[PDB]
Amino acid sequence: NEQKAKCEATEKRESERRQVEEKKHNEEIQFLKRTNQQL
Amino acid sequence: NEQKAKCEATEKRESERRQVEEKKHNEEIQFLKRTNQQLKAQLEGI
Amino acid sequence: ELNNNDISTFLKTYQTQCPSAEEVREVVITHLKEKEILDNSLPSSIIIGPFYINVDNVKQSLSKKRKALATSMLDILAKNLHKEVDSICEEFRSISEKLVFLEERIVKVMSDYEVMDEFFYNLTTDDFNDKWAANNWPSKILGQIDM
Image (cartoon, rainbow over all chains, first blue to last red; front, top):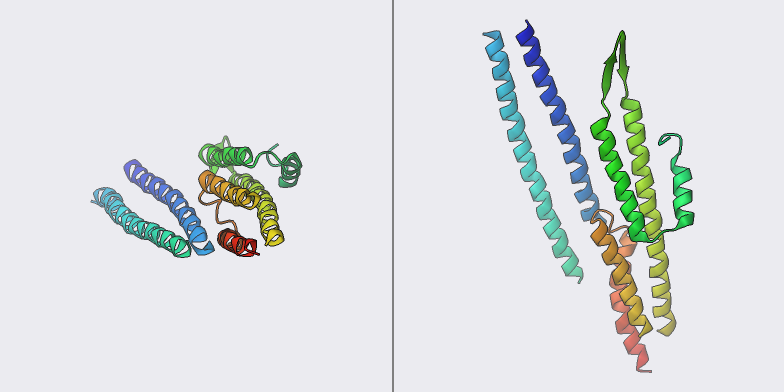
């Protein structure tokens, strides 16, 4: 039971990290998008 | 078997996550290529 | 204090100070690093004794306030650039070496903003078109000088 809960906690932790990186990627893209379109 | 399948679920979740990250990274590099086209448009102005 | 000392207070204080635009950028990038500091330091949620606490609303409010401040400093720096570009174009119109020094001014401030952030630069389509027109203006100036 505890090892299952730990594995769940690990995949939750990684999916959180993935979201943080997703939003970094999104704003980085938005920077390129705005500068490219502004020409 | 559930617990092994669960840590394997973490492993294949990683596999699909980082391969997704890698293809969206390839898309981001293609957006850098669009920024090279942006440079080409700037010089087309110059 | 970062919440209460709102965008208006610092924006007015800075822009009446009207510091040197590159040093203004250097503080706005310090505030962007303050965004990064917040985003690393602040949790989403924390557990305290019998309590479950969430801090998302402060995390986002502080970070987006910092963004609004940095971008409004960039905006007034862009307006000061526009003031220079307008004086430069007004000189090109009026005489149509000082004109070349005004080319140097526009090129210099554009290059400064480019250097201090590529994303800060290209501030308006008007800035791109004024840069190209500022290149075109010397040809007109020389044509009229023939007179």
